[PDB]
Length: 93
Length: 93
Image (cartoon, rainbow over all chains, first blue to last red; front, side, top):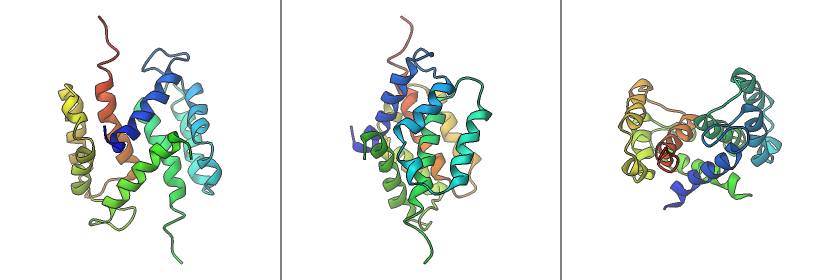
């Protein structure tokens, strides 16, 4: 159980605890997930100046408004917010 | 710095350390990333019986053989392997 593998495990726990809402186990409504991503990463979206980056993730919700997201999507969007900030470190002088 | 936000941070560190290969910082070759995912999640692909699941992730590499992947893709495929195992817990009797 390395930290690398454990890091992902954390995404499973949180994803589940929230999957108990309207869904059942692996099911999760977009309405609930929409707040989830920002609920755990409320700081990131606060340290990111990229307005276009958040816009893409915001509108993306309307694209999959199907009423249900996907775990694979939960892990991709949560990170998309982080990388949308680290860029601050690497930049031209 | 909550554990939830820290979990994702781990993906950034590993992704970077490997981005120093042929790439530079945010760039990473598929050839190197291909081994990366399995290098850190060598156990998962060992505890997963889903042959079709791994097949999709395996062929996916040939699809983006462009020679360079994407961070967003690094986080989505690494997890795809985990979820391809947890299912063992939830199942019909």
